């Protein structure tokens, strides 16, 4: 509760919280507590990584979705994350799908959600980030970068314009932007469309002043065909996209799911998604010749999970669902185990392990 013991949180606190509140209420309370610093490991130089034009104290970040409106950024750094990504944020505010829209699958250490981009909107997030803009400038310079994930409104008629608007409004406040076109919960959120979309996004980005010019990454699904991945890699290299976030939640339902809510509509996250994501990272790393930075996401809950994605090609990793089951202590746990594994496997540091599986 205030100490920081992994067993207490995993075995007592978290289980009790879930027994008292529904999943969405639990998340909202989580955001409140985090934003208030109500939280329970020292990063070694081994965990430091330099990519996307920035230094990262450690390669473990909080995935988009936990802090959709940028309300708990500072609390998240306090929790131990090497970098924070907020969003997705839509141009105009919107409520998202009706409740219930998030479901726990305890037996699978997984979650299914269909929020549908509930967002305070660009304007509100912009002011919220501006209020701590200088503080973030010092955090970034200190190895704690900030990412902003962009989405689009449900009733938007010009997808590309929605993202362009996001680039113009929040781009100046972020170290990196994410073009999220892999959410399974928005209408119909492709080589042709992607090229057109990203060309416009990059042009908008290049039009920003130097110190306010963020890297641009594309977040993709784990349900892509081989052709889709092949085309994405081609477009990425063609336009000079700075990086990829692999992956978002899956619309598939892997055989073996035990949770009673396994058939709810939405994207599945957690352990059942882990390896499908790692494999997607492996494939994208190869298709891009290891020249395009990858942020690996999907079922990371331990040092081994993180290292597998790093060895597969990820320069950084993110987690979300593991936090909902184990609580804040999982962050230090993952970092401590990653450090130990790097040593055991002969890597001088995280950097040396990036893509290691491909050079064996
Ligand atoms: C409740 C919930 C909400 C999410 N919202 C977003 C979002 O707004 N934008 C986004 O790009 N990803 C979103 N995600 C996906 C996560 O960022 C991540 O890609 C995915 O959950 C896999 O990681 P995990 O297995 O560690 O949770 C969300 C996930 C969950 C569980
Ligand atoms: O985060 C979520 O989106 C979801 C769930 C969840 O339980 N999330 C939580 C809850 C408390 C969390 C925290 C945060 C900060 C501190 C915590 O310890 C406390 F309560 F003692 F102060 C616990 C973190 C989460 F990610 C349930 C499924 C969806
Ligand atoms: O907001 C949602 O419903 C959502 C968006 C996204 O990108 N991924 C996800 O799992 N849910």
Image: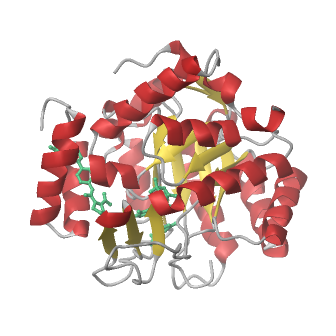
From the viewer's perspective, tell me whether residue 330 is left or right of residue 297: left
Kindly identify the residue that appears in the image at 51 percent across and 37 percent down: 304
Using the image, determine if residue 277 lies above or below residue 112.
above
User: Is any part of residue 77 visible from this angle?
Assistant: no
In the foreground, 109 or 233:
109
Residue at image coords 18%, 56%? 29
Identify which residue, 268 or 30, lies in the foreground.
Answer: 268
Quarter of the image for residue 334 reads top left
Report the front residue among 26 and 144. 26
On the image, the x and y values in percent for residue 19 come to 12, 64
Position in image of residue 42 (x %, y %)? 37, 17
Q: Residue at x 19, y 51 (%)?
A: 14
Q: Quadrant of the C terminus?
A: top right
Residue in the foreground of this view, choosing between 65 and 319? 319
Is residue 41 shown to the viewer in this render? yes
Rendered location of residue 71, percent (x, y)? 32, 50
Scheme of image coloration: secondary structure
Does 31 sit above or below residue 111? above
Name which residue lies at 72% across and 40% down.
Answer: 293
Tell me: 29 left or right of 60: left
Instruction: Say which quadrant the N terminus sits in.
Output: top left
* Quadrant of the rendered image containing residue 230: bottom right
Q: Quadrant of residue 156?
A: bottom right
Q: Position of residue 142 (x, y in %)?
A: 48, 20
For the view shown, which residue lies furthest in the front direction?
A: 256
């Amino acid at each position: 509760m205030a100490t920081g013991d992994e067993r207490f949180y995993a075995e007592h606190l978290m289980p009790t919280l879930q027994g008292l509140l529904d999943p969405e209420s639990a998340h909202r309370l989580a955001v409140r507590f985090t934003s208030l610093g109500l939280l329970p490991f020292q990063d070694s130089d081994m965990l430091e990584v330099r990519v996307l034009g920035h230094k990262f104290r450690n390669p473990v970040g909080i995935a988009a979705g936990f802090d959709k409106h940028g309300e708990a950024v500072d609390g998240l750094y306090k929790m131990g994350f090497g970098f924070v990504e907020i969003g997705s944020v839509t141009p105009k505010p919107q409520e998202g799908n009706p409740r219930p829209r998030v479901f726990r699958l305890p037996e699978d250490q997984a979650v299914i959600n269909r929020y549908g981009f509930n967002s305070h909107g660009l304007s509100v997030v912009e002011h919220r980030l501006r209020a701590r803009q200088q503080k973030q400038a010092k955090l970034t310079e200190d190895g704690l970068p900030l990412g902003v994930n962009l989405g689009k409104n449900k009733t938007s008629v010009d997808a590309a314009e929605d993202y362009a608007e996001g680039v113009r409004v929040l781009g100046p406040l972020a170290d990196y932007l994410v073009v999220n076109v892999s959410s399974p919960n928005t209408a119909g959120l492709g080589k042709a469309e992607l090229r057109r979309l990203l060309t416009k996004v990059l042009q908008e980005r290049d039009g920003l002043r130097r110190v306010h010019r963020p890297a641009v990454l594309v977040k993709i699904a784990p349900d892509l065909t081989s052709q889709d991945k092949e085309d994405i890699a081609s477009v990425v290299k063609e336009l000079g996209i700075d990086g990829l976030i692999v992956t978002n939640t899956t619309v598939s339902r892997p055989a073996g799911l035990q949770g009673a809510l396994r058939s709810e509509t939405g994207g599945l996250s957690g352990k059942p998604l882990r390896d499908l994501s790692t494999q997607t990272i492996r494939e994208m790393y190869a298709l891009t010749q290891g020249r395009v930075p990858i942020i690996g996401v999907g079922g990371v809950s331990s040092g081994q999970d993180a290292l597998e994605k790093i060895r597969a090609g990820a320069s950084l990793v993110q987690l979300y669902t593991a936090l909902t089951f184990w609580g804040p202590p999982v962050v230090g746990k993952v970092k401590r185990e990653l450090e130990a594994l790097l040593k055991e496997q002969g890597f001088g540091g995280v950097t040396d392990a990036i893509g290691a599986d491909h050079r064996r």
